[PDB]
Image (cartoon, rainbow over all chains, first blue to last red; front, side, top):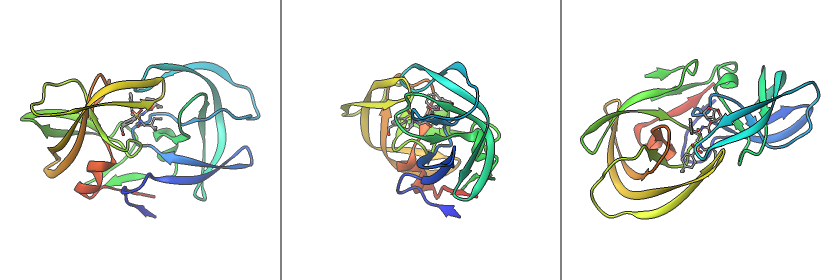
Length: 99
Length: 99
Ligand SMILES: CCC(CC)CN(C[C@@H](O)[C@H](Cc1ccccc1)NC(=O)O[C@H]1CO[C@H]2OCC[C@H]21)S(=O)(=O)c1ccc(CO)cc1
């Protein structure tokens, strides 16, 4: 689809078998989701945003479906204000900016 | 143009008579620029993201030229680590997401 930006680009995602809402975020290198239980091993990591750095759980090679488009990649879980889909998965679904 | 997301979507902008590099950020409601001395009146504001909040100065009706496309609207100024072009100006230059 073509998505205009007069509203937040929110989409439904499916991860770990559960549906959630997420923000398509071209300003995020990484995908960061709010606290949730995910299967598989994880490693502690740190990521920095506009307000400072937070600790996250890094899940590698996680299956995640974004508006019916499949992606498999790194998902960070931690105290983010909003579920964000970052460029590491936006590239996998073929997302581009156009003007 | 069409911008892929393999790398950060940085473009050259013109504001207050200065050329800068800024992110085309669909995850940002409003535009936020690194510290700079703009003239005119402003209003204090706090904006939040990963890591917490920063204090910024809100200027209204600021002209920014993004890759030759003119846009005028709210520009926040504060200690952000990156210049961020948010949706309030992305819509004005005709920017869309596509996949
Ligand atoms: C509330 C939703 C977003 C935060 C969750 C909003 N952000 C824009 C986002 O694109 C930032 C923009 C950004 C980019 C680099 C450094 C600071 C902020 N990217 C970001 O935080 O990505 C992190 C995950 O991937 C990594 O790679 C970049 C940092 C990490 S934000 O910078 O905090 C922000 C911007 C403008 C406003 C005013 O409307 C309010 C918040």
